[PDB]
Image (tube, rainbow, N blue to C red):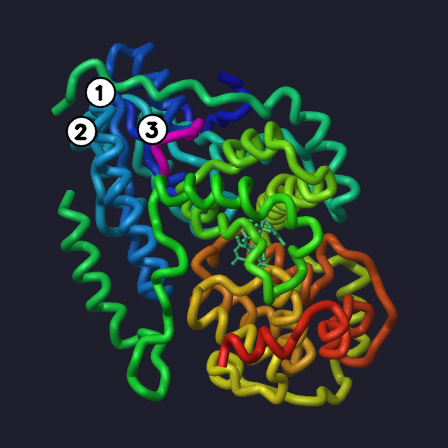
Amino acid sequence: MNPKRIRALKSGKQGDGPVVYWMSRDQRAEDNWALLFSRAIAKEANVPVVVVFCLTDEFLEAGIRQYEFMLKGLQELEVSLSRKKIPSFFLRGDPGEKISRFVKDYNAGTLVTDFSPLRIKNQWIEKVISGISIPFFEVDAHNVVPCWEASQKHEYAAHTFRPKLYALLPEFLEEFPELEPNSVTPEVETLSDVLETGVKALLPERALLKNKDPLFEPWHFEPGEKAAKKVMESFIADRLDSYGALRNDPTKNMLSNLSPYLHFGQISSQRVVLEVEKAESNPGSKKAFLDEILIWKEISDNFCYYNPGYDGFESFPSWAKESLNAHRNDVRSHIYTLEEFEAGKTHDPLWNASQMELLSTGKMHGYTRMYWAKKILEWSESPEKALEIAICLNDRYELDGRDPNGYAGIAWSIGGVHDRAWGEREVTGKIRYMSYEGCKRKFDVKLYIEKYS
Ligand SMILES: Cc1cc2nc3c(=O)[nH]c(=O)nc-3n(C[C@H](O)[C@H](O)[C@H](O)COP(=O)(O)OP(=O)(O)OC[C@H]3O[C@@H](n4cnc5c(N)ncnc54)[C@H](O)[C@@H]3O)c2cc1C
């Protein structure tokens, strides 16, 4: 167990009670460094380990598609943890008040949580730190190489972060030890009732079409830790050989479809890398898939961790801020409102088809995700308005939304973060441009539009 994966958030006197794992980002029992580190400290203190999850008040800012996907995986996780004699407690409310009350009520000895560079997680950490007196640690269980160890600053390009991450792969790319169960079972509400009351509160804002029928189709991705492993096994056996050649074709289902599991932490990215590395397939396809799940995935955490305003215009590179400022007063071809973007009522059938795939499946194709956001910048009144519209529609309808990948992905498309300067155009400036005619020369756009009417 590498001590470089764990950081100390607050020092204090350790109590004589159970070690608490404040689970948040990595919702899984297997291949979880944060849960394994909590079990090791629990063994050294001759005390059991407990898992605590907080059902926050911000769930109403999303939809039923994310609430059901997360809770149905937590129901399976509670059974998995119970088989390891590890009790799980699901609190409802503010993490600042619930975690502080749980630590005092249960005589917690040490508090451990997983790492997340998002602003809302740092908001919870500041509140919990102010209300506890026991040691507080955090463990990077989402990245193969810890986010604070891969780079000590913001990396402006993938060609500068790739050699840093690959040089540390021989040290941090390792097999996971088995989660040892608690020696004996130690001393809030049923998740089925929390799911029923939560869905009832989200029903008035459910995405529907004109026939009052729901738009979301929940049979595309089954939630859970067991279903995540089956999707990974199917990708290595059926789709990994053709990933390098068909990853940019939205008409082909050649992607791994692992992002909804990778977002909620239902499967470990280090586990996927370990199985892909030992798989015999196309070397160009393995290099392309490892460049997405390792470089681009962990450089998104590096972008959110070293840029406080990762969701703002100030985080864009200087060349892009100067270019977008010089074209602020350019007359846009079209100006669509948030409701017109949300309903897919633009003049572009390819953009509307990309929005319908987002509304119906909760997972838009990776290639169309770039064209979907770059047209928001082209058809908005300002780059700041384009950021708000792109972040709103991403976090609301994408099953993998509210993720550092989404913010770093939106920043790449609109602000050119981790990109270079291209030919200077009007409105968009030197930001990389994606045209409708360019997509037609890359894939069958007519089949993608007809699939999502
Ligand atoms: C406008 C826009 C919005 C996006 N929204 C999200 C989002 O809300 N949540 C999210 O997790 N990703 C987002 N992405 C990144 C990317 O599109 C998705 O990660 C990818 O499509 C997820 O589907 P997949 O797992 O089948 O892709 P795969 O090709 O099978 O890759 C597997 C994993 O590699 C990682 N990965 C792949 N592509 C990227 C990428 N471009 N950036 C970062 N990591 C990547 C992901 O972790 C992904 O799960 C967004 C990109 C853009 C341009």
Q: Is residue 141 left or right of residue 422?
A: left
x and y percentages locating residue 204 in the rendered image: 26, 76
- Give the mark nearer the N terminus: 2 vs 3: 2
Q: Is residue 383 above or below residue 16?
A: below
Question: Badge 1 is on which residue?
Answer: 17
Answer yes or no: is residue 314 visible.
Answer: no
Q: Distance between the Cα atoms at labels 1 and 2? A: 7 Å
* Mark 3, secondary structure of its residue: strand
Residue at 66% across, 56% down: 246
Amino acid on which the number 2 mark rests in the picture: Tyr
Q: Distance between the Cα atoms at labels 2 and 3? A: 12 Å
Do the residues under discs 1 and 3 have CB atoms within 8 angstroms? no
Residue at 38% across, 19% down: 178
Question: Badge 2 is on which residue?
Answer: 106
Q: Is residue 429 left or right of residue 255?
A: right
Give the tally of numbered discs: 3
- Give the mark nearer the N terminus: 1 vs 2: 1
In the figure, residue 57 lies in which quadrant? bottom left
Magenta residues, as a range? 28-33
x and y percentages locating residue 447 in the rendered image: 60, 75
Residue 63 located within the stretch drawn in magenta: no
Amino acid on which the number 1 mark rests in the picture: Gly
In the figure, residue 152 lies in which quadrant? top right
Q: Distance between the Cα atoms at labels 1 and 3? A: 11 Å
Q: Is residue 190 above or below residue 221?
A: above
- Give the mark nearer the N terminus: 1 vs 3: 1
Question: Badge 3 is on which residue?
Answer: 111
